[PDB]
Image 1 (cartoon, rainbow, N blue to C red):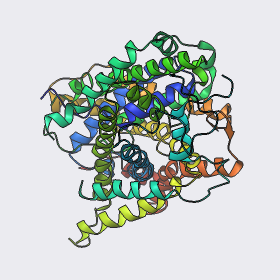
Image 2: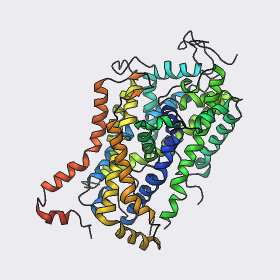
Image 3: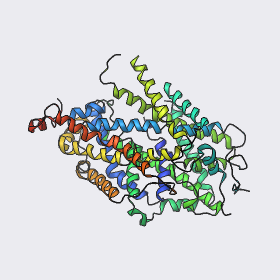
Image 4: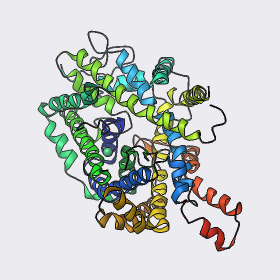
Length: 504
Ligand SMILES: [Cl-]
């Protein structure tokens, strides 16, 4: 077919504009492109080829080729387990936004309600002036607190919204369903461009500021954005696919995702220009630098359109569909992955329920009055950050050096009929492991505290929690190496020979 439908998700329309604005905009595109061509394509091709060659799931696929490096198989599951916990919180806010839109006038368009303070200004017909949209996002949807040290009470309204999300996916495609996001994204893009003052937002988006490139954060959260959007170190090995066009896929599939992210991001910054023009405030400080950005720019565009409620209900439906089509795959893969002993057969209907309840109660802690602060730690340390950089290094080293790139190339040529260009092999051997290690060391040397919204500075134990969350997935590989060395064959090159020959 021509429409794969596997070229979009919440990682494209929610995360990418969030990261670009936070890092300063414009200067974020240069590290993005470097990772895109030299660490985004070769690794994706390696995952797909390795998955299809063995026709076998990731946990045992590494046993087939890299018996010493089983820690890669276990590391991806821990990252996926962390991801399922906080990837559904976004659908908690989307449902809450949707429920408020089933009325004539949108509550966030106009000020003068209980949550709005005395500083509300319509700006549609100026010191310490706030837009009504930001007040709606912060005071009632989040009810932000002073800091992480105040967890506070639990938001009851958000609690049941999360319950609904889970319930719906406990039972979790037509062409119209697949092309629904693209039509809506185009409609939103048209409205933003024609808006007055959008030229500043585009100039802010494209023209880079080379002074900020020296900051280690920009490099860390660009390549990690590439890895997160592609689902590279979260389970990507596909047994299905028969004997194919694996190389031809990335020239079409694993590159067009970046185009969608770029186009979708283009729409948001057009709206941010209009708000800056209206309020007469620099684009740098016109909005919130945290995760809650797609909930401040998109509602403004939807309330600047005729028939506002009709457009309002649909876009949140698009977000709900995007989240549902992406989390059920992960929750199915993780449950299937733990089934490798098969003690007995309602096992298929018991683990699926057991996993959901644990995730619901552990996803409930970030729905309280101090939930945004803990959500920020989850987004920066678990399922991202150093966890993806570390695993990507060990993946390319084993196949590139231990197993042998030339042997793998021969198998790929056998499978598809021709040998891919030699550039990919050099990537695997030197480029990706070197760049990832360099970024790791650069970030470690110039360690600066992470700040929420560039205002709040976390306490010591917050950074400690983040570091433990990263280590919980970063420490599976050396531990397995030590265990395998100590047990089975202990010493001498005999164990070294056994721990390198692939399974026959
Ligand atoms: Cl992306």
